[PDB]
Amino acid sequence: RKDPIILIPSAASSILTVANIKQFLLESKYVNPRNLPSVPNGLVNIEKNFERISRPIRFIIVDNTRMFTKPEYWDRVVAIFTTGHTWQFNNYQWNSPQELFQRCKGYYFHFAGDSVPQHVQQWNVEKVELDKNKRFKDVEVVRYFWHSLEKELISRGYR
Image (cartoon, rainbow, N blue to C red):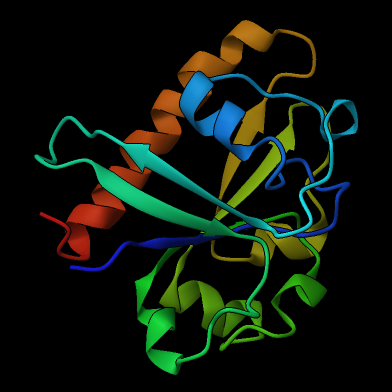
């Protein structure tokens, strides 16, 4: 069966972008986007081996929907990373957070000590907290993220 899709934000300011996503999800290190080039094509592929899943899963990670040529591709979106700007969702199949996050699992990544915006608290999104100063804490954060996503994959039939 087909590769699952993760949608992430395009704004180069966003905590996580196509520039630092692989380092974060695979190497277990947050890297500030300013210290990296921009990635114009807004696409990266990654592969992940899960404890409870037999075969490695190949993820398509995109910060845009210009390649969503068929509406059926929206069935393959297993996660959405959000910064809390609804405009991110403007060109999505489901453009309101209420509808979108009933359809796809949402994640809100931010730093501890930074207030989560009013509207984000109301959203059906899982909040994930990074440490401002202790980069070693990323290891636990990333393990937790993959544990969470694994349950989502299993629920969607990826075993």
